[PDB]
Image (tube, rainbow, N blue to C red):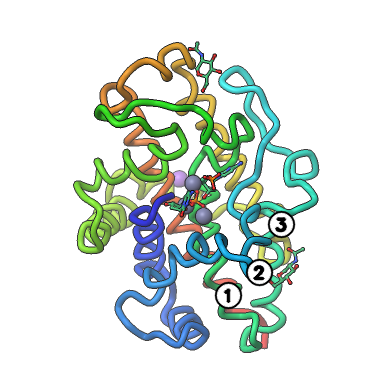
């Protein structure tokens, strides 16, 4: 996601973690503000574009070698690659937090988990084609951009009604109520089914495979003839909106559940 989407995921997670989880995270981050997770949600995207952080660029995605829109699927060995991927990073950084929660590595590990659980839920972060859709140029409300970027940024910002922090917080709030009592409330139990703190690869693969299904059902279903040539602020946005809203909600809820498990490590 872009900045607003990561902030939204983080605020959702803040609303669903247990209090002891909040304390566990605030202690690592050195921040007990109202925005303790949101303040670090976008960090990994800023860090990766430096000499120090470049090793972590692969950790934002898993380049599924499927054939969308006619065939979607993710396979960890096939798709992760030797430089690593979102799934391998969730394993590594989760295990750092389970083994070494107050060592020097914990702070970055936590910021990576907050960010990457968000990224796994953006379907094009679970797809190889054209570098996760970065190579597919499109027009969005008259602007030339690419398909990856509209899923990260243009469409979530349109749906939220802006780009600023207050806009992200309002959007998170909306999605938290959909989880608690509204349109996602009957599904949220399923969203945490299968979560296993002793198996971060399997756990995060549930989420990656889930998000990847939407590559075929929503991202690329229209075909590139249409996608390359039509302004995607029209019907493409209209049908995409409920999909990315539910995926952002899932990301925040799953992030909260995962943080609860890390903070509850037997100790
Ligand atoms: N050439 C680029 C492309 C993207 N980004 C940043 C801004 C985007 O919002 C973010 C996207 O990261 P991710 O795809 O991991 O969500 O990375 C950047 O600084 N430079
Ligand atoms: N195979 C890839 C390559 C990139 N990205 C994401 C991470 C980058 O932040 C963003 C923009 O890519 P780039 O850095 O190539 O401009 O897209 C992705 O999800 N899948
Ligand atoms: C795990 O994270 C540490 C700290 O960033 C890094 O040194 C190491 O290479 C990572 N390992 C894997 C397999 O991602
Ligand atoms: C769509 O654009 C891509 C480049 O992003 C190109 O390879 C492909 O041939 C185009 N397809 C159609 C049907 O226009
Ligand atoms: Na249910
Ligand atoms: Zn992102
Ligand atoms: Zn992205
Ligand atoms: Zn990222």
| Quadrant hosting residue 75 | top right
Going 56% across and 66% down the picture, which residue do you hit? Answer: 112
Q: Earlier in the sequence, mark 2 or mark 1?
A: 2
Q: Secondary structure at mark 3?
A: helix
Camera-nearest residue between 76 and 194: 76
Camera-nearest residue between 153 and 244: 153
| Quadrant hosting residue 210 | top right
Q: CB at mark 3 closer than 8 A to ligand 3?
A: yes
The residue carrying mark 3 is 88
Going 64% across and 86% down the picture, which residue do you hit? Answer: 104
The residue carrying mark 1 is 108
Q: Is residue 133 left or right of residue 163?
A: right
Going 53% across and 57% down the picture, which residue do you hit? Answer: 117
Q: CB at mark 1 closer than 8 A to ligand 3?
A: yes
The residue carrying mark 2 is 93
Q: Earlier in the sequence, mark 3 or mark 1?
A: 3
Mark 2 is surrounded, within 10 Å at the Cα level, by few (under 14), some (14 to 19) or many (20 or more) other residues, namely: many
Q: Secondary structure at mark 2?
A: helix
């Amino acid at each position: 996601w872009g900045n607003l989407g990561h902030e939204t995921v983080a605020y959702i997670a803040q609303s669903f973690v247990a209090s002891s989880t909040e304390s566990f995270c605030q202690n690592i981050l050195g921040d007990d503000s109202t925005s303790y997770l949101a303040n670090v949600a976008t960090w990994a995207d800023t860090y990766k574009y430096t000499d120090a952080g470049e090793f972590s660029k692969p950790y934002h995605f898993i380049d599924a070698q499927d054939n969308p829109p006619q065939s979607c699927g993710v396979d960890y060995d096939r798709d992760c690659g030797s430089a690593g991927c979102s799934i391998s990073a969730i394993q590594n950084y989760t295990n750092i937090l389970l083994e070494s929660p107050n060592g020097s590595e914990a702070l970055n590990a936590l910021k990576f988990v907050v960010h990457i659980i968000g990224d796994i839920h953006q379907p094009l972060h679970d797809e190889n084609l054209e570098a996760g859709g970065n190579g597919i140029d499109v027009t969005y409300d008259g602007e030339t951009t690419n398909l990856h970027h509209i899923w990260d940024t243009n469409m979530p910002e349109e749906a939220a009604g802006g780009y600023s922090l207050s806009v992200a917080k309002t959007y998170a709030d909306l999605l938290t109520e959909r989880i608690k009592t509204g349109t996602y409330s009957s599904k949220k139990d399923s969203w945490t089914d299968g979560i296993d703190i002793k198996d971060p690869v399997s756990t995060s693969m549930i989420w990656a495979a889930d998000a990847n299904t939407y590559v075929c059902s929503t991202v690329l279903d229209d075909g590139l003839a249409y996608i390359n040539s039509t302004d995607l602020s029209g019907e493409y946005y209209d049908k995409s909106q409920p999909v990315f809203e539910e995926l952002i909600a899932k990301a925040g809820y799953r992030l909260a559940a995962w943080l609860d498990l890390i903070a509850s490590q037997p100790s």
